[PDB]
Image 1: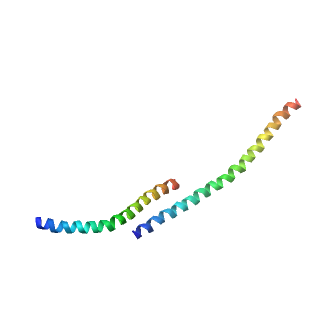
Image 2: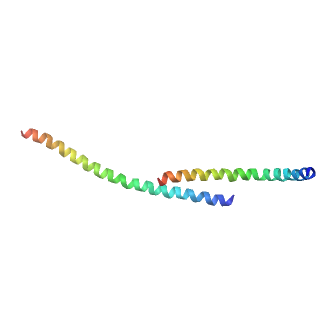
Image 3: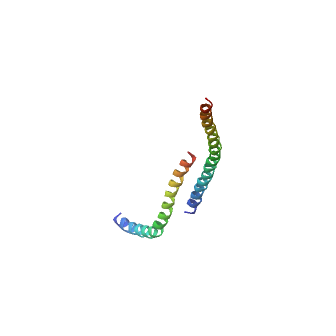
Length: 58
Length: 49
């Protein structure tokens, strides 16, 4: 019965190690998403500016 | 054999029920722990995946 408790705890340690590295990968992705999403926002604003600018010139 | 069957199986039933009383509790202890491996494994794979 004691052996089975040593066997069990080992599995749940790996559950945490996987849990941490899985959340750690997603954590890095998050920053990337927010980096570019801003850059795309910057692009679209500039896009709309030209769109009306070119009209108001003509 | 009927003497043996009587003598032996009465001893067996006493040894069994004495063990069972002590060991059915420890079986449940050991068997409910086994079920924890089967869930500790199934989560392990989904996290690895």
